[PDB]
Image (cartoon, coloured by chain):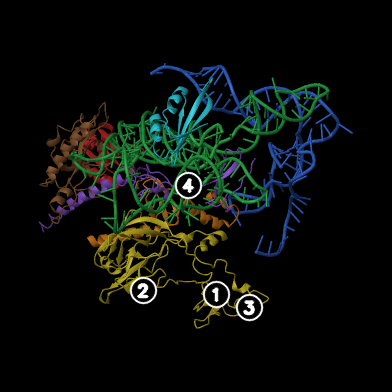
Chain colours: A brown, B cyan, C purple, D yellow, E red, F orange, G blue, H green
Amino acid sequence: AKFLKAGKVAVVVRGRYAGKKVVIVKPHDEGSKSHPFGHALVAGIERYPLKVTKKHGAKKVAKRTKIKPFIKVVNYNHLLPTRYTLDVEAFKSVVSTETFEQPSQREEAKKVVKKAFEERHQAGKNQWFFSKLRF
Amino acid sequence: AREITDIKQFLELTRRADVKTATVKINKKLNKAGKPFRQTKFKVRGSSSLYTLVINDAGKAKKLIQSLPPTLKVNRL
Amino acid sequence: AQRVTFRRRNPYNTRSNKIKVVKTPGGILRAQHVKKLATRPKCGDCGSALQGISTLRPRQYATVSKTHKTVSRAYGGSRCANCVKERIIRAFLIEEQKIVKKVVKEQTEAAK
Amino acid sequence: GRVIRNQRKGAGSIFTSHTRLRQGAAKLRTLDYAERHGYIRGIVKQIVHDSGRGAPLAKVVFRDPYKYRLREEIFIANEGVHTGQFIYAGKKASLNVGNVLPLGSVPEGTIVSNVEEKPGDRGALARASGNYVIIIGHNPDENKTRVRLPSGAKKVISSDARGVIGVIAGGGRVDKPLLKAGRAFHKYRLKRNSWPKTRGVAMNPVDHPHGGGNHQHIGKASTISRGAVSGQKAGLIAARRTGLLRGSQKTQ
Amino acid sequence: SINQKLALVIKSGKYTLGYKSTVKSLRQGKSKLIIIAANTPVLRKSELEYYAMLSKTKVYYFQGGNNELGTAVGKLFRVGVVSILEAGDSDILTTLA
Amino acid sequence: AKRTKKVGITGKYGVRYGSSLRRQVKKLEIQQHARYDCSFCGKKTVKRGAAGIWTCSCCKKTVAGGAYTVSTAAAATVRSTIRRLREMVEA
RNA sequence: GAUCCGUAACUUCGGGAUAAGGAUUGGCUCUAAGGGUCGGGUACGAUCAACUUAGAACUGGUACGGACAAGGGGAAUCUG
RNA sequence: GGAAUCCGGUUAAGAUUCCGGAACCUGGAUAUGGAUUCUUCACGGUAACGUAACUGAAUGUGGAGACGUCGGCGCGAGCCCUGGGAGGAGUUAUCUUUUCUUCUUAACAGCUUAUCACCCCGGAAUUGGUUUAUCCGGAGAUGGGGUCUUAUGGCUGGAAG
């Protein structure tokens, strides 16, 4: 079946986000008058939250667990699809084709993904997604 | 040893407080097929590099030497 | 037909004593001493020259900015985007197989 | 007479080994805790030509068990190994080509090479190209192992001495004639200094026990005793037979 | 034999040879079966088994190298993986293959 | 055309060295200068680089082997001995 | 020297071998062959630039690798 | 092996060393601008990767330094050869739009520039591409579109003074 779906977690293998884990937000299985190949709209995590222990204080536990996200159109061949799944409905509306092309919308959409991803990592749902892949 | 192409970037160079001196070099050249014309070179000497501004329009050259600061030790030719 | 000399007191044709003959604005030939050529940096895995990195003699890499000696990726000026690519494939699949290798032994200890 | 040539061989002036281009001493890993209790896995990174030697050498990198660093050892490449292979060094490792195991953990008839003599001397026997020992038997009490050396001489050694399974690469090397004095020149150019060894019968009575005469002849028996003296040992030292070997030398 | 079964899919079914067209047909859910040669690299074989389990596709392993897998598909080059897009009238789907 | 009758590669030695010595060289210089099949990628690209070193052009894997051929006759039976001796352990 | 012809015994079949042995060779005037780049909707022509080889006529006190440079060759014996 | 200097002029004899102009390196303090930041530690490209920047100690890994010889091929530099033109000198009983000669551009810097290599689209037997030399392609050729190394070359600055 078509496993590249709108909740699937992928791992980028090519280009400035290589090794950074993403989740497919909108699969475009073929074509565009833009990017003319099978491409997916992914939301990712660029700077992973560091490991936190009992030793870290109240303003260090906040500083350790910040999340820098990114949003990206990426080729299917530059994705390694995983078995993992992440909820996507919190930023389904914000990330679209209109989000790119006008970069002013890009930063106003990156904030929603940061608010969403940090809301998962606190009360730590989806443990595999918020860990840096080691290579 | 570096050409400056923006004429307003050349004018902010002259007040950079190390440029004590400059020079205006005139070269008799031709405009690519026939008749001669007057090109002028505005060379300011910075503390570590020489900036050059070539001006082909000899009218626009006249509006630039008045735009030089009155303190610059301008060496004509 | 203007013959030329060395300019330093090494009169031998060594590696450090190369000569290119150039014309000066005095209208004469003069030799100029050319340094030895820079090699490209090579990839740490495959050994191929890795692109986007400027090729300088090794102490000249301290005069240039960061973006002449890197590309924008994990393992920038060290590995070559295809050894990085197989590194992510290999890290993902073995550590996923280790998740399989954990629980496939958890049925043997549950059924012996 | 004067000092003859093989007595000058030991003073080590021009007769030392020409060891610039050597890659290093080919050695097994030292017996740490991992090598004698379980195993450890290294990666063969490069198969490389070492000057003065016929066998190729293999850089095998290992993870240091006690410090975060990498340790590169230089093995002799057994025949079949390739760069990128995982090599398993230790007691409880598997009987594959390339894995170095103690001799007590291999069955009888296992063909190993680079085998230690004392457990811990990092590789002594069966170490030139093509060679191998055969583990022919175990004595599990007083734990010993009878092996057969490449010269056919049988030897009992410790069952904790290690060795790498397989034979050593570059074998069949000496089946090609050198054809030239240039190839023998370049052969011994990276080993020592004894290429052009003028026959002792063509020298003078100062230079050798064989020199002189109005014909080129040895004059006395060329088989010299073991209890002879440095300076007399020119010929066949302690020869228990001479002439062409007809029959089965080939010791049982 | 298995080589008799493949010879009908080449002449009466739909398929793709090569790696980049195979994992494309995994991503589209268009593959029915993939046959991997024996001498494929283990990392390429590991993701082709991973792309199958994301699509619930069955993996068959050929009993030979890429020189003799390209022989069974009737071609003079060497193929590393063949991906059956469509069983035709052959029976690779319904057999142990 | 067919340039030499029987000397083959060893015609570079000309008339020297003795014919039976140039015959044993021709047996091995054909073997060490030939291209062998790679075990890993299945291409015929493996060429010798030095005595006992056999490198493949594409996939770049360097395999250790015999001095003039990739697999010697001695080490092939060794690999099948240790193959036999290992399956007496797992069985 | 170069070009063309012709090359033996013997051989380890690679050589021997420039084997041995012959012919030609200047100057001038021509002929022929060997090339580059440009425009053809989805058969050719303009033009430019090379020294190489072969041939023909004429010519001279039969001369011409005109100085320079530049293998003597063969039939064997001893020996390494 | 190696941080970094070139041109022009000058002396009775010195010069990559002096003089005029124009650079670069190392060590050191440092001030201002640009950049980053309310998503704290930059964004763009599918990607190769781009850039005026764009924090990163311990420790670890890797690259450069760092490398044989011969052969042929491609490219560059200088030299040689040659055409017109602008000067000068020679020959000129006769001839010769003739014989000789000057016509140059450094280090350094900005833009651009390549074999190789890599990326995307595509999926090839009727096998195709291609070297002087036969090697490459389903482990993805030919093809279309791109990215990089800047040896090297072109233009401009240096610089016609």
Expressed as whole percent of the image width and height from the top left, the position of residue E14 reads 25, 32
Instruction: Name the residue nearer the viewer: D16 or A69.
Output: A69
Expressed as whole percent of the image width and height from the top left, the position of residue E31 reads 22, 36
Mark 4 vs mark 3, foreground winner is: 4
Q: Amino acid at mark 4?
A: Leu
Mark 4 vs mark 1, foreground winner is: 4
Find disc 2 in the rendering and name its residue: D155
Expressed as whole percent of the image width and height from the top left, the position of residue D166 reads 35, 61
Q: Amino acid at mark 3?
A: Pro
For the residues labelled 1 and 3, the Cα–Cα distance comes to 17 Å
Classify residue G76 as left or right of residue D152. right
Q: Residue at x 14, y 50 (%)?
A: A59
Find disc 3 in the rendering and name its residue: D205
Instruction: Name the residue nearer the viewer: C76 or D239.
Output: C76
Mark 2 vs mark 1, foreground winner is: 1
Q: Which mark is residue C37?
A: 4
Q: Amino acid at mark 1?
A: Arg
Secondary element under disc 3, as helix, strand or loop, is loop
Can you say whether D142 is above or below B32 in the image? below
Q: Residue at x 43, y 27 (%)?
A: B64
Classify residue B50 as left or right of residue D67. right
Dot 1 and dot 3 within a common chain:
yes
- Chain containing mark 4: C
Find disc 1 in the rendering and name its residue: D8
Residue A85 visible at all: no
The picture quadrant where one finds residue D45 is bottom left
Secondary element under disc 1, as helix, strand or loop, is helix
- Quick one: label 1 or label 3, which is nearer the N terminus? 1
Instruction: Name the residue nearer the viewer: F36 or D92.
Output: D92
**Dot 1: few (<14), some (14–19), or many (≥20) neighbours within 10 Å?**
few
Expressed as whole percent of the image width and height from the top left, the position of residue D225 reads 51, 81
Q: Amino acid at mark 2?
A: Lys
